[PDB]
Length: 121
Length: 121
Image (tube, rainbow over the protein chains, first blue to last red):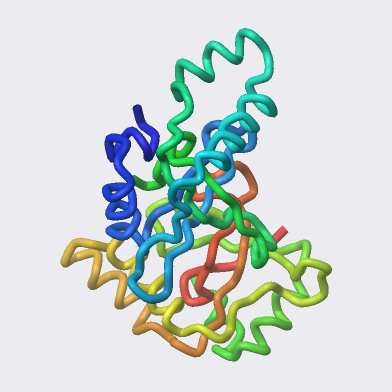
């Protein structure tokens, strides 16, 4: 697909490398939400790696379900959702990020690589 | 076309007072990008003063170099760029602004006063 998780072929080390390589330019758009917010990933002041939460399949499942339920909530929309994104990848990490919108100083979000596309890749 | 930073005497309190005085009648066109998009100056969350960033001249250099490399990245264009804008002024604040409609980079941009010209209504 065109999502970040497919672009790195479902591999957390490659995801971490990808984000690290484009630290100064990289933005992510949620395409699983109706309101196409673009987000700036958070990086760790130290080693310069992205701030990822690894191995929390519980939170992954929640975010996955949350989107399906909020935005793709009809039998029809549901078949397309699954066509676009596939079944949940419980092994993906969660990316720490802030939405590019006004007054975003506090705002942290958890994004699934499965649901985001790089801007400008 | 005289830039905002020139019009306010390269003084950062002068810049703040200018955006306060013209609130509601000025927009800002980014003239350092290929597409010269017009944005609206963001005012502080519960608002009198413009939402500027004044403490970070590494972010100033980042945005100045960013446009140079993206948009003026031939020998010819780099000359025209420099002749037009001059060296980066590290004393300038960063202007938080938002697009007038849905934008590929999201709904918040950082604009250099050195790279923008006012658009009046």
